[PDB]
Image (cartoon, coloured by chain):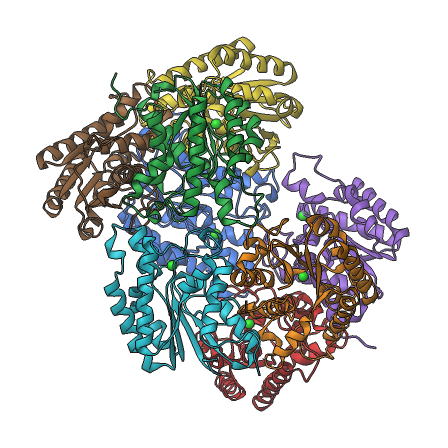
Chain colours: A green, B cyan, C orange, D red, E purple, F blue, G yellow, H brown
Amino acid sequence: MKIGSGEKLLFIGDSITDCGRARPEGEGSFGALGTGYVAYVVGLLQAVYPELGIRVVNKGISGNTVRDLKARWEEDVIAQKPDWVSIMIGINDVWRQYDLPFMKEKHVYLDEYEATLRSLVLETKPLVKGIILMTPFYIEGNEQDPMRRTMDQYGRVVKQIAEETNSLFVDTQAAFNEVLKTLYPAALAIDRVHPSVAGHMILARAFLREIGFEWVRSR
Amino acid sequence: MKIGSGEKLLFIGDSITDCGRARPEGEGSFGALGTGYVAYVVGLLQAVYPELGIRVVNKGISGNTVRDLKARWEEDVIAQKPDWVSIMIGINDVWRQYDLPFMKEKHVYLDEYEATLRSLVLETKPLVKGIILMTPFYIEGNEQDPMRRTMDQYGRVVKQIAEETNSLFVDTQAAFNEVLKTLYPAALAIDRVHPSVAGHMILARAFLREIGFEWVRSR
Amino acid sequence: MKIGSGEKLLFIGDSITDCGRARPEGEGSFGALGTGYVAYVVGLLQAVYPELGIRVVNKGISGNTVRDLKARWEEDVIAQKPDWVSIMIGINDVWRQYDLPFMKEKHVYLDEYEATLRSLVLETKPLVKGIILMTPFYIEGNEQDPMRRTMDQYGRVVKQIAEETNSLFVDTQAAFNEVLKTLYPAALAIDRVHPSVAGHMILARAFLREIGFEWVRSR
Amino acid sequence: MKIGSGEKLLFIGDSITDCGRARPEGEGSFGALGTGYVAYVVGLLQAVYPELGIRVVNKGISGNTVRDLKARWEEDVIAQKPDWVSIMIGINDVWRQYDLPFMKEKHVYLDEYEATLRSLVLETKPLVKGIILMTPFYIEGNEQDPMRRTMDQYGRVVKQIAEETNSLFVDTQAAFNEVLKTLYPAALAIDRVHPSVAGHMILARAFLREIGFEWVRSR
Amino acid sequence: MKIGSGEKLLFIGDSITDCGRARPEGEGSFGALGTGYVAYVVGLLQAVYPELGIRVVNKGISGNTVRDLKARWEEDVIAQKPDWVSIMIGINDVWRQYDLPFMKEKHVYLDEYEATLRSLVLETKPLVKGIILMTPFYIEGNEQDPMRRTMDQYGRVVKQIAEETNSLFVDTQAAFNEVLKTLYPAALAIDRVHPSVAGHMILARAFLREIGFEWVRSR
Amino acid sequence: MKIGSGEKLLFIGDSITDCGRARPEGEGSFGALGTGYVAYVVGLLQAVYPELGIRVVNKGISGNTVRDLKARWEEDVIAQKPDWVSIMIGINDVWRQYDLPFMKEKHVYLDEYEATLRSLVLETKPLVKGIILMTPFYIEGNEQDPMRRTMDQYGRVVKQIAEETNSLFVDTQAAFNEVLKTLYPAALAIDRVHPSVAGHMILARAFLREIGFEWVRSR
Amino acid sequence: MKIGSGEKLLFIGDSITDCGRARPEGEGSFGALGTGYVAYVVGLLQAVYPELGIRVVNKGISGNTVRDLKARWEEDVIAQKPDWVSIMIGINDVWRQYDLPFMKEKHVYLDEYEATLRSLVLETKPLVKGIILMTPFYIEGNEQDPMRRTMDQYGRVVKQIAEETNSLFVDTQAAFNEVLKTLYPAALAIDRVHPSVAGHMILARAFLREIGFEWVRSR
Amino acid sequence: MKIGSGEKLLFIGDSITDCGRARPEGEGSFGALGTGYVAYVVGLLQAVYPELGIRVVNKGISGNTVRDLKARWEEDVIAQKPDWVSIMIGINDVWRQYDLPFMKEKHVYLDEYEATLRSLVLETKPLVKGIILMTPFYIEGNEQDPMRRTMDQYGRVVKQIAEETNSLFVDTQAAFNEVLKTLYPAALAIDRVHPSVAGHMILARAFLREIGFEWVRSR
Ligand SMILES: [Cl-]
Ligand SMILES: [Cl-]
Ligand SMILES: [Cl-]
Ligand SMILES: [Cl-]
Ligand SMILES: [Cl-]
Ligand SMILES: [Cl-]
Ligand SMILES: [Cl-]
Ligand SMILES: [Cl-]
């Protein structure tokens, strides 16, 4: 378990992270953590490692791009003095290119995305024990579907950045791809982005695996 | 214009047709028709052919497959004594196979779909002045996506039944496919089924063209 | 098609234009465009000219007179940097004279109306590619009904102004008059102002015809 | 005062009479009567003739034609054992011909209207102490407007039936026509049917005058 | 009719006057005038004197004493530039003495009431054509009931003031007393203060009689 | 304490007893009892006699007269197999004579009231361990007010029936009358019927005293 | 009765005291006092000592610790100029240690609690006639349950402070303990803190006993 | 994994199982399963065993005891033709003895509980592929608390019935007891019954472990 006792773990990102969490503080309880992967992570950590006393904050905001995370970073991350920061961003940065293809300033293209996300990691890294970078995802099994293909480019940037900055790394697309060998996207997410409880469990498990969670602990 | 003065035109189908129409009666001019292609069709006919004196009934019901249509056909179609019946069904017949793949009783497979729709058309045809068969559709430009591929199969059945019964036919998939050369699905419908105003216009226009509507009447 | 690719088309006026659009920005989607003629115009443009990538903003506000448009012109029009501005105003300017006949300062009489609307066009014209002036209307077939007779005076001023300023021009009263040869006003609008979907289609079609829309495109 | 002590007075009609009255019972003093002319009539009688001890029932139902009145006449009128029955019906009988011109089954034409209303009056008359027949009305000052012209015809039928049956008669059209020499319809009722408080007062006053109400009692 | 053409008549007082009127302007329509005696007055004036074009404003506020009227007089009366001001206040000034008998600073005793109401009349009188002073009331027939007995003291002060300042005068208690010879208070007002439509008609008629209203006009 | 361990105590009456209790069951500890004297009685018994193990059912219904009690007596009382039945009825029996004086069928006059209540008590008495008869009341200190005078008459009937049947008796009027030496009715109940918390306490205390409750248990 | 005529009694504490009272003033009526022990106290005082004319204010706020009371003391207590202050605090100070055991700064430990509560009493005492200190409580009969055991430590501090400062003193835990010899906590409070009406009566009675209330007065 | 491909798994129980599931059908993937352990179980199975193709039905109903289960067993279990039935019942059977101790008919004592649950298991077992019996639980670490002591007794019955019938068994009490070595109940469930997300995870994990779930599949 990478996370130590008494430490503060802060999650930020878009609606997948937000999942209706309490604004502004996103702590004090679960209703406050929302009803998606963040809550599930915290539930499983408390169920299996109750003695850890990990404090968890949810700063997701629906609709955010990486450009939006930067604009609120000081107040919503730095000022919170987290020990661990998990970031999952990029869905909107890409989605806007496909749902509003003629409003191009709402689009965050890959080179701006890369430099901005890099900037967040570099700023934060000296201040925390660790960073976990989760890739964005798109629940679509065809690598050549345009939005899937773009999403994968963004996820490769995330992985680049995690390697270079020694951050932890969760390939959420890889976790979905495995399930997509069986299920058509509709069975997980009608809009290919916002998943069922099952999709949130896919995400939570992928995050827990990267931080060394054990489903049945050995010592 | 295939529809002639004084006639009663009855639309039946699923949510795409329903679009919040008034239940049970579904008529006429002031919101009972719902807020999608059916209301637009009726709007445009009134704007351009006010003297036709057409009455219009919306018997769409959210969720319906062709099995559901059969179960209420006597009360919602035959007992309304329509002159013209337009049918657009198959989206749920297909979609349940993909979004609830293990709930097989909810699925209406091609054999049930062909036999049922054929039977409804054959029985209705001598009771009415004419039938318009609209294909189902899926807003997805990749013919090899599995749900699009199945939807196209269901559409072939509709086309074949219309030819065999000398019904009017609207290929709604072809109408979307034209726009999908420019737009990714997300620009028209986040779930690839329930479209924007623009998608409802694609549908209304495809319906109108088939019934001989003119935007500006030539004579 | 007068409107070119990537251009911004801004609609302003009263409740007929507003039709419940999102405040303040009236863009980002259709819910944002409201549910009347503006939305229908945008739907039809996207259905038939999806490659245009026209951006459309709705600045209608319910209850407005031309005196109200002027008071918000800088923020709601100039600051938006539109390429095309469509104006439809005058219904309230006239209606107040008939529903509050003893509150005369709520009335905008024809000479103030003319100079004010002229002032808006002259200010705007150097800043945009084009202006479309739509007349007000009153859904009433008797030319001698007092409010109809006043409305027609205002519509003649609009046409004057469009001619003199080389603006495009939509005679909405003419479009309604044709339909009123068949339908009594009640069938279109119970208050003779706020129309059914059919009346909104009358308006949208009249606007589309003036900007060179083709229902089936020729090249 | 034609109404005498201890008597039960029952008003029936459409929305103009209903005005949100309590269903099914429609009585008595604290809001069950609704918020239009019926409540005003009852108010004024109580203010000026408190000792009359009149009981009042409101059986108005929004939407009703005379066909609808016939269908519930036994339960809503005869079974209430009223002493006096006031009827105001015909607005919807007529209006449906104009607002839904192609839905002919919703229309109640003059032959059905005369025969039905005649029959209801003839049957009720020997069961009760008296009947008050109020004309329908349309708030429109042009006798040649088509709906006003039809409404006036329906009113003649009411007048002729009242004379033939020695019923009291209130000409509600004449009462509006007097005010319409000063005001355009929009100042009293935006849809020309559902009036302001002032219109309900016009109605209440016309009713009261016919039953021999005095504003200040002479003796 | 004391009130002349085009003049502005402003009503102020407590909940009996307010009766749910629109804040802050209490004009522009009837919903804006609330649903009690003020609205009825305006309805009757418009029904019988539509050509007068009287503008009517309602500044009642629920819970007010005369101490509250003074605190808002400049903004809610003077600044409105009325031609006629009707005041009805004193119910709360007295009620507080009986429902909160141990919170004595919420009480406005008769000498403060008198001087304050006098001060309002004297301030206003040079600025307007006329003032109408309506007494408070208490719907209770026993002169010796403590609250009735106090209310009557306040009403005698009102009458004093009207005489001395040449204001018009409406004894609302006298109008209720007459009806209370027949009806127990419960039949008019369950709390002996807030009346039924009948009680509001009692009030409206008493006001109309004092300003010279004619139920059927003679010239 | 007249009520003994393990017994079921059932309260029936009108709104004073109801006070928003759960329908139909009306039991037990967590809000089903409503928010007036019945809940307070049950609260205090539990606070001071927790070991008594008393079960309590609230069958009060807003609006009821003794006629209404008779109509549901079999299902709401006899079929509950109570040990003790407390009845408080008569307020509406009387009040309808005053608030709806001309709706005579709603009135339950003294002959119907005595005969009915007598009959209910006689029939119930051998089926249960005991009966508590509570008078109705009116919060009005003037014995010569007409509704108070009638209420006192109805209370005499209750007292006489309790004596004749050896029922326990609570004179609720006497309990209010004591407080009314200090307070005007408005301090306890604006409508003279529905009291504050303090009035419900007056009632609860009067009930408790009659059943031998001790505030501090002597032994 | 310790409390004298015309005096102001102010209650402060957490949700047990607040019980939905009106913010900010918590006076003017009962709705304003909320629906728990404070309201019951006031009801019983008014029922039995109506002539006292005691003014009662409720400043409870849900969630408060003693640290929260101090932060609002000047505005919510001192500025109110009470004659008597009742304080009940400590439930949250302790609860946080058990429901958020890893957010230790939300915890108020016993030495901070003691000094803070002492500080409130010492500040206030010169300004008022009297102070009543109510212990916190926990509805749990096992003295060795951890939260019960902590609560008792806090209650012993309260008693210490009351003795040293000559404050009145209510041991709410003692009052509950007696009832807990019969009832399991669930029957009083599902969360062992927020009680039923019965628990609120336990509290109100314990407070009334300490201020010398008599259930039936002797002079 | 004890559950095998294509099978239907049906969960029944009380609120812990219900957790707001869709009534009556309780299936499948998009919210119909509710928001507690059942949805989590289904989520995790899908994340880790998507190919199993398991269908899941939630027939939990808030409030139920085993008596309630018997009454709807035919329609809610047998008629669903499940392959696997999981039962978790006993919490209310027990809790009613403690929260409503004097309402003995609401209690289901050990004899009724054993006989009923035994009978339901014996009857169901030959109709289905397998049964999973989950104990009830109480989140309370003191074995000598009276409700915990009774709950443990009911759990022994469940364990004994599962052994006798060769059912799978989940000891939910043991799963909570492990976490209760660290946390006081209030950190998991304020009422000791309805847990947080973390408690639902404790339950889901205990269920999954018993059916042979692997967090990471070995082969
Ligand atoms: Cl988002
Ligand atoms: Cl659908
Ligand atoms: Cl408007
Ligand atoms: Cl109507
Ligand atoms: Cl008031
Ligand atoms: Cl009642
Ligand atoms: Cl609290
Ligand atoms: Cl439950």
- Let me know if residue D80 appears in the view: no
User: G45 or H38, which lies in front?
Assistant: H38
Q: From the image, which quarter does the N terminus of chain D lie in?
A: bottom right
Please say whether residue A61 is visible from this viewpoint. Answer: yes
Q: Is residue E30 above or below residue H114?
A: below
Going by the picture, which residue comes out furthest to the right? E126
Give the residue displayed 80% in from the left and 40% down from the top: E111
- Does residue D91 lie above or below E93 as drawn? below
Q: Residue furthest front?
A: C219
Residue at (49, 70) in percent of width and height: B41
Instruction: Give residue H216's position: percent from left, percent from top.
Output: 25, 30
- H128 displayed left or right of C189: left
Determine whether, in the image, residue F111 is placed left or right of residue D121.
left
- Position above or below: H76 against B176: above
Q: Position of residue C144 (x, y in %)?
A: 74, 80
Quadrant location of residue B119? Answer: bottom left
Q: Position of residue B169 (x, y in %)?
A: 38, 72
Q: Position of residue B171 (x, y in %)?
A: 40, 67
